[PDB]
Every structure is written in C-alpha cells, then in structure tokens.
Amino acid sequence: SAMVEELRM
Amino acid sequence: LNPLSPDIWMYVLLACLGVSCVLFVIARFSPYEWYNPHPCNPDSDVVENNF
Image (tube, rainbow over all chains, first blue to last red; front, side):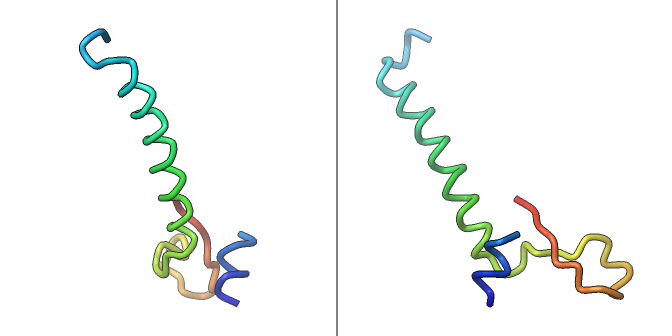
C-alpha cells in the first residue's frame, strides 16, 4: 500500500 | 572554461543529472515529505507531493 500510494501519485 | 579539462565538465553534468534523479527516487520512498498542504485544517487527509 505504501509503495502504490507513493508511486501512482 | 579551459582550466578544467573537458573530461570533468561532462563528468559534472552527468553527475548533476544522476544526483538529481536519485534524489527524486528517494523522495518517493521518503516517509514525511508528504506534507498535506495547508495543514491549518486537518479536515481531509490530502496527502500531496513535493520534490
């Protein structure tokens, strides 16, 4: 969740 | 620009590009750079970017 949240933005 | 030999000039340009890019990479992994603009109102968790 952390990587996705800070990656897609 | 004669003093520094043409080697170091291009080395420095490439180093600047690489350092900026790795800074950008570490910015995403950073925990606290996400700084919810205008935290005067904590109403919404608008987690937004910098760097």
